[PDB]
Image 1 (spheres, chains in turn purple, cyan):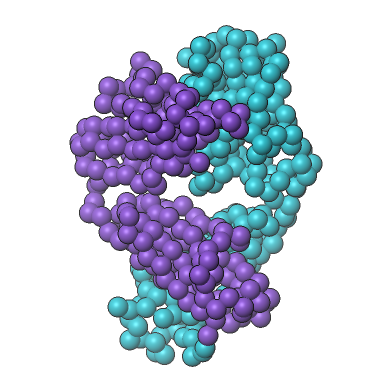
Image 2 (image 1 turned 180 degrees about the vertical axis):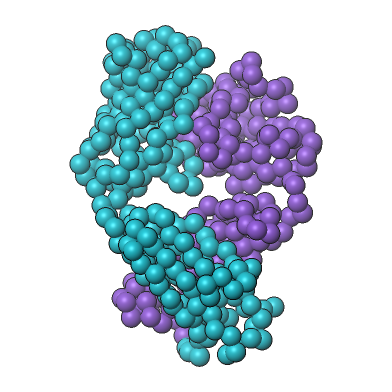
Length: 211
Length: 218
């Protein structure tokens, strides 16, 4: 539980705000904290006990709590800022700490762009190799953040999926790949398979079938 | 200043155990609640367990509750995590963190974790396949199921590398790394230009040359 959006983005000096929502079992009663994890270094306590900063954190990094959801506001964004965040809290019912779905705050350096999906169907060979590997090619998007998940026909499922993380490319944009490995027969039966690349509110569901 | 440096991780065939190790050096460890957090590649952070300053009570997340064990040893300011029955999903990076003094719900200082890798494999090679092409279409090669990480690619031995990008692999469940490469060309130049991928996997001492063709099928 505890959903933050996968995204946010804004200009080299403007404001922005990431949300956090869970339930009365958590956030609603228990104190919330927020962490900033740049690409490869470790995380850094940004805000704690709802609105508190460790002398070491600017005043622009603020944070409130309304009901069963907390929000981390930020103003005057700086390249510095651009990193991933996480809103965490303690859940009284599961007796164990909880982390957030995470959010990537990208500070606009170049014009947005939509992801270029390109779903490849199983290769004739591999199929023979008693295996079914579906490739969903994703590319050329500025805010390097998207969401991937598949759907065998009507219904969706994750049983057998593995998606990479974005990664900058020559042309300055990000680009990542998903994978839906199957059993050649699972490939046969279900009359339809689609790849869903949600991104910036607007999604894109590319489908392809056996024939 | 504070200092926490994890240690003791790497590669381990599923099941048998392995113990991680964190060492504080920047305060009075003997009086600080300790935390274990891990992060798989890509997936966010997942909380694991917590132990008091004297190692009496501790809370684990069902996500392990019993598969793991978090003991500490204040005499040598070292924090531990015992991992028995290493399920594959457990592959990730292990962050060691110190919770505040009067706010155990606050991890103030973490350290660059240490990488865990639950994979029962030993050197293998590539399993190249053709991503039949179809403004102007794109096509590629689908390398799959290799164990030793390093693996490079090229198309036609270096003829205009533009319009190409080879993604990062991915540790599938079978603890096998797979990755693909892709190219873009004039959909008008189908059946006139020969496109093939110059694959390469040293750990397997292999080169591969799959020559992709247009899908006159279905």
